[PDB]
View 1 (cartoon, rainbow over the protein chains, first blue to last red):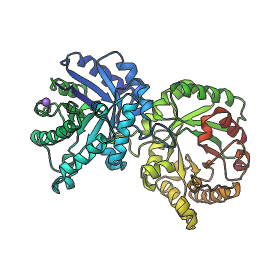
View 2 (tube, chains in turn brown, red):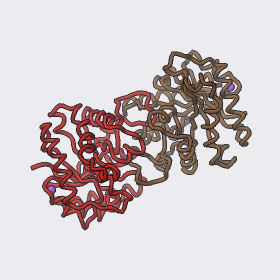
View 3 (tube, rainbow over the protein chains, first blue to last red):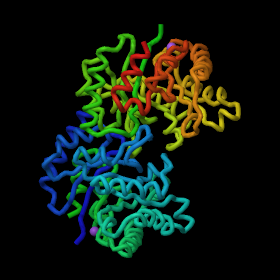
View 4 (cartoon, each protein chain N blue to C red):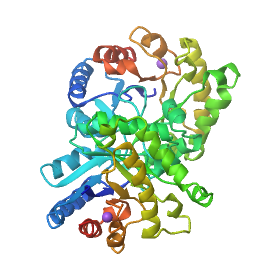
Length: 248
Length: 248
Ligand code: NA
Ligand code: NA
């Protein structure tokens, strides 16, 4: 029995007063979700203090959407895992496809980010995923395998047991193709096998493609999908809670 | 006369209790500095709320070390200029050499960041600077000129009159080489001419190389150097205030 999780990635959205509305609604609605679902939100850096003040003591966790590969130094604009941790955050997303694409983050850089998260007392949500070109070239397993291996290679098994992994079907996001639950399960089963070989087979594997209120039950019903890293639906409390309830 | 400014770039340093100590010392010391010097600190994103609570109503301004090229969207980890503005920040650093190198930010991306900063009511500190390879190839003017032109091209003159520009001699970093005051002036005079041709000739031009208590007066005495964007010396209140006082 592995941990079920529904974690919202707000991405670059939110201002103080809209954040307070979403956070109150989610905290109030979360009381009605089955108690085995770990619910969390990852907010933009400046609002970590707000998320703490509003959610502290409740069942909703919070986190950042990135952390630096280093603990300190001449890295203008970057935020250290140690900084995020001081606001009682539980999570840090590392290696999101948007950052691998737009910021050029390599497999090895993501591995360093995972380690920094752990060292600071956060649970890293380690994102992996292949592009359309990669999938059509038949290299899905080589790619997401190399991404995950790079992270596992710098951790002991006991450290690896503490991560979360998220699969993003980048090939189905704004390309004209779409993913089925079965196609998701196929990659999750592959990733589960790599985790087991490391001795981290119990780690939560979250689906990070398009998750909406109408498809959550089908996706989360798959045997190796333990929940979701939710995009746009995480911005409207009704949709987000609907998704949280489907993870029972 | 143009606005004299000394702005500390903390880079990726600081935790809550050390931040409070530095902020207190700087605010207290700032009360004795000549009143024509605009003193500011740019802090990591999670501490913008802390800088506001501690500095509000005083003469020390605060800012972020970056802002997104976009106002909102699917840009996991990125922080919008609007978000920074809600914490009463006056500044955002855009195009720092560390971000052009480590994050691949192009000339045109920096220009978009400047615009987002202005639209949100921040003063962007637009960083320009050439590498060693560039300087030794004789291309200093072609490079820093292109970097500045990209930002000026997307602004009207009235908009351009609101920016700050900082020159970073990237060629002096980890190279053993150093810049003289006369060399700094030569580049500033070139950048001043480009600003004047746009109708933005009154803009503050800050020197962003290595500034220490013992060299500040010589650098800031140059006719086109209006102050400094300070690195490591910004981390110790005594050294930072020394630098601030020299901008009289
Ligand atoms: Na399942
Ligand atoms: Na001067």
